[PDB]
Structure formats: structure tokens, C-alpha cells
Image: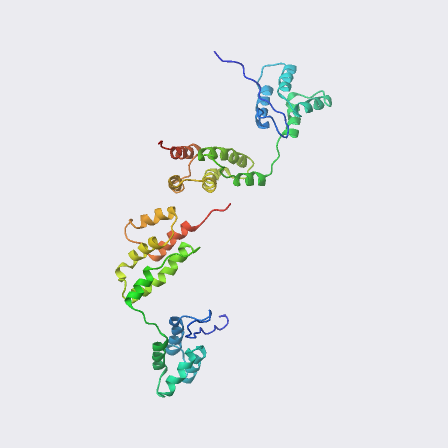
Length: 183
Length: 183
């Protein structure tokens, strides 16, 4: 049998959130689900929507409704996106990707996962053409990582051995090299 | 013409031998030869056998004979093995092999020879199956040696290029890499 009901994800909109809160992009997934999918009455949608909000973000929702009583939940979410959503230039998406380097004590397979989230944003905002993202991924790994020289021998084969690797192919080759023998 | 007669190998049985003495396993080769092969009279066998003994080991031989006058040289060597021979568990043979690492200023071809004596003992005492000794040899060299990275490139080919190498094959590949160019 399906286990315990799952708690709502949550969001404050604060300049420094609590470590249990989500990104706006993820709270907006839960909110889009509640709006589009749930078989529920409007005031019960609105009480489930309201129950997820904290911080400053809870405080906007009342102001917007009082000034327009005809507001649907589909319209109220459009006001919520303007105040708490995100604005970022093409140049900022591009510069924020290319500046990313491996940290102290971070593993190479941890770095290559962290770096892949930034490459998707830069391809959405048309900063990088989708035609060349697999070449741009390999060039940035060899630029930013602290590769051991047996790993260096393999990545230099992938650079030359036909087309550039996919994400899961590159991630496999890295994992085979990360393992150490005990003493 | 065959040159000067060869001196007897020798054994004390002492807790610290003189540096000219052999292991019991080698003095027992000379003793097994004298017992099985030499065309000689019994009291002359026994005087040649006796002449090789020193330390504490010389002192046992009299006690054993006095208590049983019917003793043959084949029976007297069986008593000698009980007191001076070697006892070692399966677990001690296995642990004593796997713990072996390259020393300060020792060469890689010197290490791979020193390590091969220990692998034969562990396969006699059934600690390591004879089916897999060539795989176990390569895994221990890459674990214990301080390989330069051009040697590392070749041993990583041998690991993948079909079956694992024999002793003399591995020893050839190592020797080709050890040599240096003068200035």
C-alpha cells in the first residue's frame, strides 16, 4: 500500500531562506500542479495554495486579491511570478557558466554534475546554440577540472575519437577512473 | 676439467644465524641428496650429515640416536624436521603476501622478483588458487609499486590486452622502462 502522505514543498521569498525551502522554480511546479490538475473547489485550491507560502511571499497574496475581486488562480500566479521570479541577461547566463571551476576537495564526478545544471540555463536563454552543447561541455571540463594524468589520457581520446560524448557516457568514463585500491 | 670440490652448505638453527648459513629449506635439500643419492656406507653418510650441522642444531642429533639405536638416516631426518622446520597458518601466508610494499631506493624489477617468492608459498599452502595467480600478481604490483607514468601507461595496457602476463613477460616490460639516458 502507498505510504504516508507527503508534505508540501515551501517558499519564503526572503533574501536568505531557511535550508528546508525550495527554489522558486520548484515551488512553482507544485503550484502549477495544484492549479491545473487537482479535482478541487476554488476556495479549497486557494487554501492549499496559501498554506504553502511563508516569509514575505505570504504577504503579497492578500494585497493582489483585494484590488481585483474577479481574479482567478491562473491570473493570481501571473502577479506572483513578476515579484518573486527571475530576470537574467543573455550575457550573464554565458559569463556565469564559463567562470565555473572545481572546488577544494570536490570530486570530478561531483563537479561534472554541478556544471550540467548551468549548461541547460545557458541553452534555454539562447546564449549557447543547442547544436554545439556536447562540444562546449568537454572543452569546459578540460578547462576547469584538476584531472590526474591517466584520466587525461582517456579524455584526450574522447576529444579525437569521432563525435563528442553525451552526459551519461562522459560520466561513466570519469567514474571508472575515480576508484582507489586499499592498503 | 671440473674445478675445485664445493664446500657443504651449513645451518645452525639459531634465532639469529651467521650470514653465511642457509634457510632450513635449503640445508634440507643437501641432506635429502646425501640420504637418497650418494653411493656411501651408513657411518660415512652419518659423518657427512653431522659435519654440516652447527649451533643448537648439532646438539639434538646425539640425543635422538641414544634413545633408539635402530634409527635409520631416513627416520632421524623426520625428528630433525619437527624441531627446526616451519609451521604457518593459511591466514598468515595470505596476510604476509598482501602486506608487501616497495622499499626506499629499491628498483621495480628488484621488487617484482622479491614478491614472487611470497606468491609461491601462498599457492602451496592453498591460500591462493593456482587458477588465478597471474591476475593476483598484476593487482599486487600496481598496488605496491611506485610506478612512473610512462610505465603506468604500459601496465594499464597489459591489464586490458587479453590474458594477464606471465612472470618473465612482466619482467621484460619492466626492464625496458627502467633504463636512463646519460648527460
